Image (cartoon, helix red, strand yellow):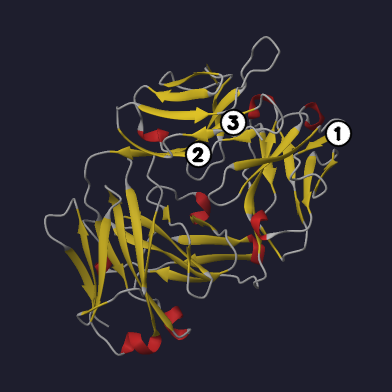
Amino acid sequence: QVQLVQSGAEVKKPGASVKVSCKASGYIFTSHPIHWVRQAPGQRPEWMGWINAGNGNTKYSQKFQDRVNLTRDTSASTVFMELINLRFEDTAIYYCIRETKFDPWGQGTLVTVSSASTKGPSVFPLAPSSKSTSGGTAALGCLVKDYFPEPVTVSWNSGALTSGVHTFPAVLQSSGLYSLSSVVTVPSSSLGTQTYICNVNHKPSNTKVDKRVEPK
Amino acid sequence: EIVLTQSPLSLPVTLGQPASISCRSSQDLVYRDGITYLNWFQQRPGQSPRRLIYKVSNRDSGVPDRFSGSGSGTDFTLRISRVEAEDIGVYYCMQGTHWPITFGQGTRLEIKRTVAAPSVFIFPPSDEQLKSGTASVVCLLNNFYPREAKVQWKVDNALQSGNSQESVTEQDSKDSTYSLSSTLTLSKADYEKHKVYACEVTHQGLSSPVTKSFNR
């Protein structure tokens, strides 16, 4: 019920601006103020600002004054975070939090400040065979190659398949592009009966792919 | 401005054994009835943080008895009676005495369990990728402990070095294991000048190395 849903990841060029959404549901929006906290890679989470969802009154951090704009859409029960003059240190995961009992935190929005071109991923099957089978268990997956920037959300059989699933953290390549693999342990008996699909979503690039991984 | 500092920054703790995390401030305690506004958060893998302790020692709703909070003025503690496998994550102390709201760096709590040897599986390149001119060979290591493992790639008896990318998942909450992916990346040209492709795996759980190979 009580949840805060954030917008998707954005790649932005230096100097530019980012606007992040945060929709409230399972309570009255105006009733509770929102808080914004970012976490830059390997840094402390940093508090950016506060907003009263009721009357729109704000309070910023000295670091974020005159760079951050906290607005609203009360009919939409959405609160906004606008950050201008994007510097390289602003590449962080941004969180919106309801004030009372500091719960719930939103899922976060990864913002990547880079000059590089956005690249959608190419999805390849990690197909099962005898060489990837141990005692009536076959391994299979997807290889989500060369994408920019992070993140890439991966799922199986439209999130109905969870057991055995290992989605690996991404790795930056020589080409400054990312790779990822998602694997799943299934019984060898299901290959040829159950379809295994892996649903890859890369929102900065607006790429969504469903890849049938079959034995060969 | 109020700088919070968490003493063990990484903490490997055995199942059933006790754990502690420290937080050093610059005197938390508002004028109002001597309430110290120190809170503890838990960020579990693939999840946004969740507040455990509030007001130094007060457990949030649904928090187990094993979690304890202590402290006065500048030195605070988070103590875990006996660690459970679901306790894997990063822990942040946060103060809300004076604005700006400030946080600790984080403390990654690892778990120590018994040795489990990994299941090895090897994936030959997909023909779809081979049509795009490149060949990736993936070697999967599944549900092992400890995290420490060694994957050697041997192309036609030549030991590869540098042209591989390993990636380890976060520790499992359910069984405290790890899964690792190793990707050896060749070009369709280099990939077709050879025949034998093998990944040799070495780990504490193994009495001898596990080699898993294939021919084209």
Amino acid beneath label 2: Gly
Front residue of A134 and A99: A99
- Which chain does the numbered disc 3 sit on? B
Residue at 37% over, 28% down: B19
Q: Is residue B122 left or right of residue B104?
A: left
Give the residue number, with chain letter if any, for mark 1: A57
Give residue B154's position: percent from left, percent from top: 24, 76
Query: Against B44, is B170 above or below?
Result: below
Q: Residue furthest front?
A: B26
Front residue of B114 and B6: B6
Give residue B8's position: percent from left, percent from top: 41, 36
Q: Quadrant of residue B17?
A: top left
Amino acid beneath label 1: Asn
Give the residue number, with chain letter if any, for mark 3: B94
Kindly report which numbered mark, 3 or 1, lies closer to the viewer in this rendering: 3
Residue at 76% over, 28% down: A32
Mark 3 and mark 1: span between their CA atoms? 23 Å
Q: Please rate how many residues cluster around mark 2, counting C-alpha atoms within 10 Å: few if below 14, some from 14 to 19, many from 20.
A: many
Front residue of A35 and A142: A35
